[PDB]
Amino acid sequence: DAVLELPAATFDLPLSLSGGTQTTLRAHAGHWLVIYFYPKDSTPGCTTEGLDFNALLPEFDKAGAKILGVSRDSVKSHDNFCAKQGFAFPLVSDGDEALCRAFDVIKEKNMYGKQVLGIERSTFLLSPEGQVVQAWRKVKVAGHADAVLAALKAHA
Ligand code: NA
Ligand code: NA
């Protein structure tokens, strides 16, 4: 029932959050976790995605689930982004791309005559026992948070 196996060490990686604290995936044991990776703070698309998740947060709560957004922007950038948009969930500053690589969301594109890496917008649903049970890759923003919520309700 796992669609992705993560390195065991992934669950103990210290994840720097907006607000200056740290978490790990293991610390979320016991409830559902949505982890949504996005390429960059404060862009039109990535802002829309975060606001879409933020608007549905009471429905996610009803399943006791929690949301984490992830990019490689700094904690300061995340703090600004969260404050300006009013997000009520944390953002991981995955500055070294450790979590991104664990979930295999760093993808290469041959453009400008060279190989360019970047975060591919992707989302994962992690069970209360830490299994990755559903994955969405190369995500288009429109309708995405709704679809993730629907899938959560179906799994939970
Ligand atoms: Na960190
Ligand atoms: Na979990």
Image (cartoon, rainbow, N blue to C red):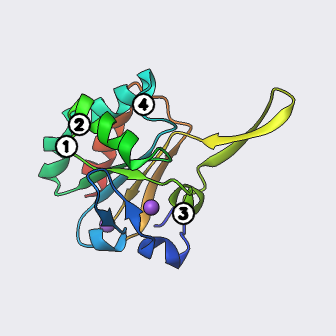
Q: Is residue 100 visible?
A: yes
Label 4 is placed on what type of residue?
Answer: Cys
Residue that appears at 36% across and 69% down: 24
Residue sitting at the far top: 44
Task: Give percent across and percent down for residue 89.
Answer: 24, 47
Tag 1 secondary structure: loop
The numbered dot on residue 46 is 4
Q: Which mark is residue 54?
A: 2
Label 2 with label 1: CB-CB less than 8 Å: yes
> What's the distance in space between the residues labelled 1 and 3, CA to CA?
28 Å
Closer to the N terminus: mark 2 or mark 1? 2
Q: Are marks 4 and 3 in contact (CB under 8 Å)?
A: no
Mark 2 vs mark 1, foreground winner is: 1
Q: Is residue 26 above or below residue 137?
A: below
**Residue at mark 3:** 4
Q: Point out the image quarter for the C terminus.
A: bottom left
Which residue is rendered at x = 60% and y = 58% of the image? Answer: 101
Residue situated in front as seen by the camera: 150 or 48: 48
Name the amino acid, label 1.
Answer: Ala
* Mark 4 vs 2, N-terminal side: 4
Q: Residue at x 47, y 40 (%)?
A: 38
In this rendering, position of residue 56 left or right of residue 73:
left
Q: Residues within 10 Å of mark 4 (few under 14, many from 20)?
A: some
Q: Of the two numbered discs 4 and 3 on the same chain, state the one appearing first in sequence.
A: 3
Q: Which mark is residue 88?
A: 1
Which residue type carries mark 2?
Asn
Q: Are marks 4 and 1 in contact (CB under 8 Å)?
A: no
Please tell me whether mark 4 sits on a helix, a strand or a loop.
helix
The amino acid sitting under disc 3 is: Leu
Label 1 or label 3, whichever comes before in sequence order: 3
Give the secondary structure at mark 2.
Answer: helix
